[PDB]
Amino acid sequence: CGKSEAPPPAQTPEVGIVTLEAQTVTLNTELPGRTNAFRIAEVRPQVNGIILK
Amino acid sequence: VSKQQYADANAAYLQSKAAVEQARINLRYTKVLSPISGRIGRSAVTEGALVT
Image (cartoon, rainbow over all chains, first blue to last red; front, side):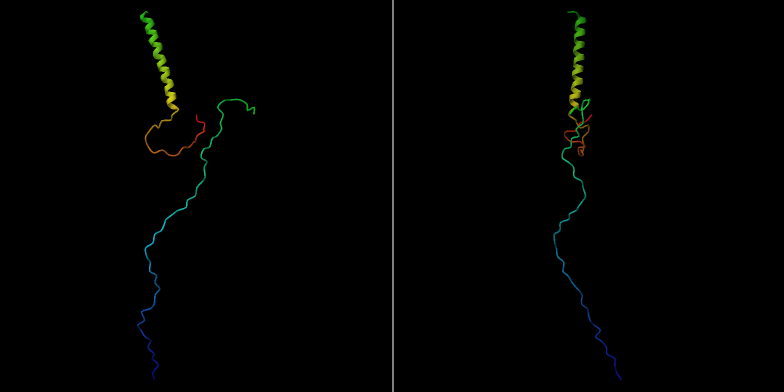
């Protein structure tokens, strides 16, 4: 009769490769913050009395 | 001069020395000397601020 049809057993299948190499990287972060003035002076009086002008 | 007049004069002299020492303390206070040695942080007030 027949009809066996044995496939080839040995395949050793294909893979995908990349070849990595040495490389320099800079590590940098990003942090929140507020802006402040260089000098702030709160004008407070040093005597007592009515503001005339 | 009497010994009592000298005893009064040097007493007034030492009282004036104590008064000028009291003034030297307040002159020393306006330069804020650091009370201990260590790491200082940041200034909570800037130039132009009124303190008490």
